[PDB]
Image (cartoon, coloured by chain):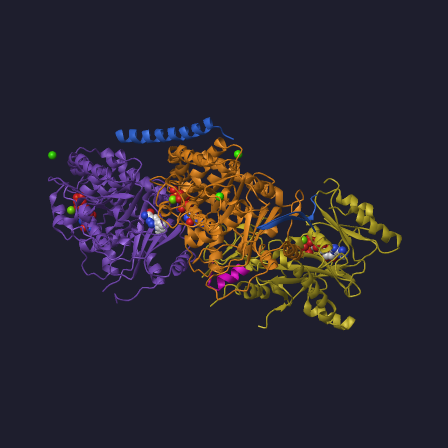
Chain colours: A blue, B purple, C orange, D yellow
Amino acid sequence: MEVIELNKCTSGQSFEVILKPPSDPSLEEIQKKLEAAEERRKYQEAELLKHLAE
Amino acid sequence: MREIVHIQAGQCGNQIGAKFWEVISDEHGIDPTGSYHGDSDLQLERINVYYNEATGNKYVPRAILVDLEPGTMDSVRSGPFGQIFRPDNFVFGQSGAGNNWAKGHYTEGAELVDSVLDVVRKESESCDCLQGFQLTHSLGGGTGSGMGTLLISKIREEYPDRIMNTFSVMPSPKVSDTVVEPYNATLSVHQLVENTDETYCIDNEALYDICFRTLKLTTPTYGDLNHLVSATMSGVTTCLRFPGQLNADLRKLAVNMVPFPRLHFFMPGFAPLTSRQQYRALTVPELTQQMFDSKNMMAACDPRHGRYLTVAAIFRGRMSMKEVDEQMLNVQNKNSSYFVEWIPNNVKTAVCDIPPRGLKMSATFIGNSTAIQELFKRISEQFTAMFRRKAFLHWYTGEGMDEMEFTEAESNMNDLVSEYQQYQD
Amino acid sequence: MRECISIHVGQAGVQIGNACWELYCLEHGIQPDGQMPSDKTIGGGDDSFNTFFSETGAGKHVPRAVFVDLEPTVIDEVRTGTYRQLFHPEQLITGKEDAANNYARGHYTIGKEIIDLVLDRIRKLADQCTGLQGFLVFHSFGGGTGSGFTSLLMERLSVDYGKKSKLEFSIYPAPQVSTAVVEPYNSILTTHTTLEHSDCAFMVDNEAIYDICRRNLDIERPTYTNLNRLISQIVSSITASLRFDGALNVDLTEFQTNLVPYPRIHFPLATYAPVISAEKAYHEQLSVAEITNACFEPANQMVKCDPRHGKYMACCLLYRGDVVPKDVNAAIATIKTKRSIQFVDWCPTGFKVGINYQPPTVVPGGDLAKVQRAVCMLSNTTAIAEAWARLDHKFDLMYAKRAFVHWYVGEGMEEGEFSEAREDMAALEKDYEEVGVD
Amino acid sequence: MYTFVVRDENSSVYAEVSRLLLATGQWKRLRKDNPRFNLMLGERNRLPFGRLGHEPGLVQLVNYYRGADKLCRKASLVKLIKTSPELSESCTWFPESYVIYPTNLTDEREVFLAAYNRRREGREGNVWIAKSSAGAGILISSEASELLDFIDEQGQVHVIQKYLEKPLLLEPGHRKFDIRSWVLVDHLYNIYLYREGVLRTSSEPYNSANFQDKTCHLTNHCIQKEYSKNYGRYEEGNEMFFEEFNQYLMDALNTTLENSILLQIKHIIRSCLMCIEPAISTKHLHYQSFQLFGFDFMVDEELKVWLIEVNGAPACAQKLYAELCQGIVDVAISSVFPLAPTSIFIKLHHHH
Ligand SMILES: Nc1nc2c(ncn2[C@@H]2O[C@H](COP(=O)(O)OP(=O)(O)OP(=O)(O)O)[C@@H](O)[C@H]2O)c(=O)[nH]1
Ligand SMILES: Nc1ncnc2c1ncn2[C@@H]1O[C@H](COP(=O)(O)OP(=O)(O)CP(=O)(O)O)[C@@H](O)[C@H]1O
Ligand SMILES: Nc1nc2c(ncn2[C@@H]2O[C@H](COP(=O)(O)OP(=O)(O)O)[C@@H](O)[C@H]2O)c(=O)[nH]1
Ligand SMILES: CN(c1ccc(C(N)=O)nn1)C1CCC1
Ligand SMILES: [Ca+2]
Ligand SMILES: [Ca+2]
Ligand SMILES: [Ca+2]
Ligand SMILES: [Mg+2]
Ligand SMILES: [Mg+2]
Ligand SMILES: [Mg+2]
């Protein structure tokens, strides 16, 4: 039961107590994933319109 | 600002649609001339969802009246609230559809479809942000069926990313105008399977059985059947027309109700349904036990014959929201054998402080149940009874159709039956 | 001094953001119009509150916040609310139609067309910082915007602010205060694409806030206002060290160092007490030992679980009020002899303790009562893995039938991103079991 | 109408509880994967506790205390006794035991040989027994070489504890036996002892000069009915109940079962359960727990009771399935889900 690093100021204080010792995607790749999902949307909507044209 | 564009096509469509605007107009404090005279600000909170604000504080419904014969729409205009509707939003022909899906969809209707969409377009261009459309119509007739589906097919072409809702009256031989209603119904249903996001099924037989048995009406009328649809339409739209912690648009509401693109056919319910012992106060238990009772359901489908994919319940009135949860949670935990176990928390509940006209409190039921397959089984059975002999086909082959298109609608809906079947087991 | 930018995404994040800045202003003595009578450096100064507030020549103390929502109805409450004067129109970004509880919508469809704008608005607050620490992101797991858009914002913030820290305040989905059904999909989608971008995440379970409001506040049916006033208290206590003088958790980096030894396990469990009903006649003020002993009860954890059957990796005790170290060590000793506190053998069995003498501030007319001392325990336990197991189970139930999957596919997402997100969670659950069970 | 589910089809005990529940017409059974339930009869291993108590409006109850395995696993029990100050290492009712890990994998090998050599040097009885939880696989031998050499031939944890070389022998027969007491613990942590016990007796004369044949040393119900040749001779099914066993104790030894053995048993059950209460209690938990236990005791010729092990999923005696199952529904289930005596249990009061 030890109290280390006792720091006291005007608005409080903080310390540490030990009981026992121990034993990304670039900006280019994100635009691609966004534009890729936009393409599958345009392709799905085109197949919807082609269906309506028939 | 999330506006809705209403459309009513055909006789049944316009008569039902008219009463609808008569019911909600009274709830929002809109008199037959368009003037507001309510007492609560909640009546105006979401008033721009179904009404366009004109000059002088006048409110003009955002509806489009459509039909191939002038008769029905002349009635609406001379009716109680007929003056409220925009004069231009009346689009009608003179030939009529003769209860022929082909005429409404291919010949007569085709000649008038462009002019109806011109009005649809004019109403959208003013919307700050359109939620989506809603069509009232029947499927056994010729206009609201043949042309109605044709409208949807063309509204989805110009607005492919807007919600398309429909209140569809299904034909029953017990409340039949013509022997060809199963033909018109089978053809429309395939269109709804394709180009609608949500479709409230409303069986005329269930409306008839409710007026006769539950309501004790000796000889029901189409007007009596429409009072139910009026009140029901008002209920399902309560969460949209009034404020609250709900914050839900048509798309978000569909996202939580349609687990599969083609199984978007719901069964609605209303409670109470009392005969004139009408002044008795209705407790929250009674409101719930009836709301789930088949005799209070309008699809003429026994829910205990299938399983619930998702369920939505809206409660109206000043009541104990704590007591609403308990009773709803009680119905689930007492009949959990009829809800699917692969969709957690598929039963939700909403409360609204403003009750309908002349009711301390009420409850509206919205169920996406596989039991609805029994509806399409009746329709398909009545279809095959006639199509196997090619009976009455000439009314359609004369309009430019081929027997092949009938065989496809037949196989299209049988597929819809099989799809609803693999999810009940 | 170093600045902290707060970001609020979706309805849940924006409403909870409203409730916190209301609290921050009451604590720091900031009036609704933004004036601060105690601040003696007019329009300038590098004090502790300046980590969250900037100052204008007129003496207005303006938050360092950014509210983002894809539909304007929720952010509009802020533009016309009590504290409308704090923010300027730049800080409030609103679209016109939301994501309909659809992760794919908030992330791809709608998110792509508004992401570059949010960045610019955030870049405008970054340029005002002499030494930006990082970002505090408030959002929900269920919301199509809170989940779909947040993950996208996080991916870009890690590109435009590589060396900066990013803490989360995430709202775990609870059926008692939700009208949606696809929330398990979103929660698991966002936790997958956000995991390598969040240094430390505090999960609050509405089900936990709900029962604390029903049990301790005697609210039969709590509203979001009720839930937010309580959640803003925990948030205040967690962000207090950044806004007041002190030496414990003085910058965002110290949160990872003190709470996250392993990266993927960056979800501390929060515990708070006491929560006393204001409507009560008059309560017996609890002692340091009593309120600390309560930190190990399940009834006041931000996520319902059983820390007795997990293992602690780190532990913090943030006190506020009449507390002295002597009293803290006394309670801790008594608790180790009565409780089951099993640590991992590769971490010290200790507690970092912070004490701020100013007791918790309570919003007048709110639901909480004024207490003379309160505490919040941040503990990294493998027991929080239960929350993931629950969620991952609901995901499996629906995905086995591809239910609702078409709504995501139809917005541009590939069906594979589901199984890819699910397998990542299966890895996250395994990491918790490798570190906890024997 | 209360609802429950079943996830352990192999449980002879709760298979009867479910049968009685449905007989009340007030409990409806559900599929084994429906989360909307009031009561769960869960599996033995890997029971998903984390998912319990998160269904709005439902008070959920489960029949397994999370963490009870510390008391029902061989090695876990020993470690619990030697590490728990409530029991201490000097516990007088638990045989001197040690946890031993096979050399192909803490471990108390050296500590065991220390006491072993101390006994071999002091002329004392030095017959130990090796066992584990992964058995039906037990070896009795007086040589430390054979015991250790037998554990290394396996691959799971084992425990070497003193063998009771002076067990109490029934007459006529000169045969060994053990005592099984069923203890139920409800959600409030009230400790109920079933008034009815059973003695699984050996039908063979105890032989101390031949541990090779393990038929007169092991009293398991399946070993006597498979490797014993006097099965069912003295009592039906090698099972004597508290009535006859009480009469024998009065005729031969001039004492009662209450005064000689029952007090020690009620003391051991208390000491064991109170010890781990703060670790498994569901007092302020989001769900409730209650579990049936099966304590196996030994008795030496000095009428001292020793603890062998505790079963977390025990079976019952054929003659006591009805009376006990009904009792489970009275104190454990209905006490939380009331329906629309002369309790058959003995409440062991304690300080929570
Ligand atoms: N604690 C708390 N939870 C909230 C609050 N608002 C919403 N939620 C939760 O958030 C989840 C739904 O996400 P929302 O924030 O409403 O959705 P969104 O982020 O606005 O995104 P959209 O789908 O586009 O509306 C539900 O589970 C709600 O319980 C709030 O103010 N406080
Ligand atoms: N230290 C010891 N001294 C004397 N006999 C012992 C003993 N340890 C075990 N036994 C004998 O072994 C039997 C108990 O074996 P153990 O309980 O270890 O195996 P097990 O758990 O598979 C049987 P169960 O679980 O059904 O009670 C008792 O009948 C007892 O006679
Ligand atoms: N509920 C209800 N059903 C109607 C009404 N009018 C017609 N129907 C049903 O609709 C079908 C006839 O369609 P109809 O309205 O004539 O279609 P139209 O040709 O487009 O006007 C039949 O099955 C009728 O039972 C009505 O006012 N109420
Ligand atoms: C019960 N409820 C619903 C749910 C679905 C629908 C629908 N029209 O699909 N309508 N209302 C409300 C709770 C917040 C939405
Ligand atoms: Ca013509
Ligand atoms: Ca200053
Ligand atoms: Ca990073
Ligand atoms: Mg007609
Ligand atoms: Mg939203
Ligand atoms: Mg065993």
The percent position of residue B212, horizontal first and vertical second, equals 23, 59
The percent position of residue B369, horizontal first and vertical second, equals 35, 49
The percent position of residue D110, horizontal first and vertical second, equals 80, 46
The region drawn magenta spans D17-30
Quarter of the view holding residue B405: top left
The percent position of residue D46, horizontal first and vertical second, equals 58, 48
- Indicate the quadrant containing the C terminus of chain D: top left, top right, bottom left or bottom right: bottom right
**Can residue B130 be found in the magenta stretch?**
no
Q: Nearer the viewer, residue A46 or B127?
A: B127
Quarter of the view holding residue D224: bottom right
Q: Nearer the viewer, residue D279 or B247?
A: B247
Residue C57 seen in this snapshot: yes
* In the rendered image, the vertical position of residue B396 relative to residue B291, given as above or below: above
* In the rendered image, the vertical position of residue B420 relative to residue C372, given as above or below: above
**Can residue D18 be found in the magenta stretch?**
yes
Q: Nearer the viewer, residue B302 or B5?
A: B5
Would residue B354 appear left or right of C122 to someone viewing this image? Answer: left
- Indicate the quadrant containing the N terminus of chain D: top left, top right, bottom left or bottom right: bottom left
* In the rendered image, the vertical position of residue D350 relative to residue D54, given as above or below: below
Residue D29 seen in this snapshot: no
